[PDB]
Amino acid sequence: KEMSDRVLIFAVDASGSAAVLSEAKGAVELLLGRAYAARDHVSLITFRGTAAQVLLQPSRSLTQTKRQLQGLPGGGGTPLASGMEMAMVTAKQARSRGMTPTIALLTDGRGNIALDGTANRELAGEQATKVARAIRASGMPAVIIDTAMRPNPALVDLARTMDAHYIALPRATAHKMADVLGAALEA
Amino acid sequence: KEMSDRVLIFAVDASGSAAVLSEAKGAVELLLGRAYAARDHVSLITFRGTAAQVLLQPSRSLTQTKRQLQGLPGGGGTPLASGMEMAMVTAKQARSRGMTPTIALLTDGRGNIALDGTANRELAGEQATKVARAIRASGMPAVIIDTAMRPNPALVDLARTMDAHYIALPRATAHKMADVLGAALEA
């Protein structure tokens, strides 16, 4: 697909049970510092309760994009795993934006609605990265949660399974995400 | 001038000095992802050896432009940077298309033919963004080249004199160029 050009559709999982989302928001602020924006279309898909926010095209200027990241609220609980895919891919790969998408599941914990069919559909957009958020899980042995997080990415899961146990961790992984995703030379 | 509609006439300098012209081609890819397809038209003025390629009128949608950028060949050497004027200000913004022009000089190195007249004629097209490429000079203190590259744009050089002493810069600078051009309003 397109070289360098990407579309970071961040599934901003805003769980209300998260111990201070400020840290996560800070990580997002750092993302744009490493990820050479403009070409990329960071879609702020705030979900868990809310249904998305910033679309692919609206992000006209970097400075304004940052204002959005900071302004992003938080609230939710029910993890619609497969539901995300539909709300993501379908409404993201539209002609009024296009470009090579980059699915980023920032989902916290497991998902209640089974994925299954979505896996077969992933191939349409590709690059389904899985940020193993264990925010709420930090208070109890996840185990099963981890097992539910693993079978999310397509080909080459390991290179997309970015850990995020505590909200403070994402700040470091944020960099690695951009660097790796940039060199994503597969199809 | 009016908003949205722009004529990004990019002087795609294809000098052999620019090791791996791919970066120059990719720079346009990035810009397109930020530009307003259909309205804006990036002219692939591959001049330095070849006599240009893609004009403003032909390419309509992003799906057309991108593939052409990649398909673009390469060839050039003689420092005829100044010669671009006629090929741009005259041959591009002709009655067969017109629309709000924007001169983008991606010229590599200096130009033996004095600017003078061309520089004064800039006002006919306006917005002569200068990209200070110097790949051949990446291994030695250019200095003189830098001094010949600076006095190229119209009023306020700084906001148009985007450096490119090495191919690694263009892919990054493209972000600054894109976002700024999106709100380019002076006359």
Image: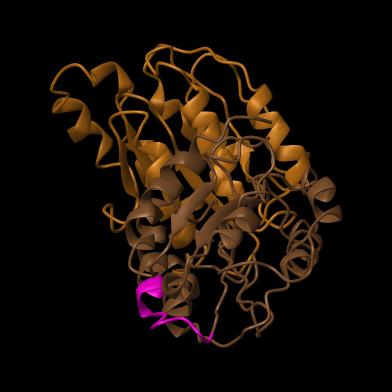
Chain colours: A brown, B orange
Q: Is residue A145 left or right of residue B180?
A: right
Which residue is more in the foreground, A123 or B120?
A: A123
Horizontal side of B66 relative to A13 (left or right) equals right
Residue B71 appears anywhere in the view: yes
Residue at (44%, 48%) from the top-left corner? A178
Which stretch is magenta? A16-25
Image quadrant in which the N terminus of chain A is located: top right
> Residue B114 appears at what percent x and percent y?
30, 27
The percent position of residue A47, horizontal first and vertical second, equals 64, 77
Quadrant (top left, top right, bottom left, bottom right) of the C terminus of chain A: top right
State the predominant SS element of the stretch in magenta.
Answer: loop
Is A28 located above or below residue A6 in the figure? below
Q: Is residue A127 magenta?
A: no
Q: Is residue A9 visible?
A: no
| Residue in the picture at 41% in, 60% down | A32
Task: Choose top left, top right, bottom left or bottom right for residue B69.
Answer: top right
| Residue A121 on image: x %, y % | 83, 49
- Residue at (40% x, 38% y) in the render: B170
> Which of B29 and A32 lies nearest the eye of the viewer?
A32
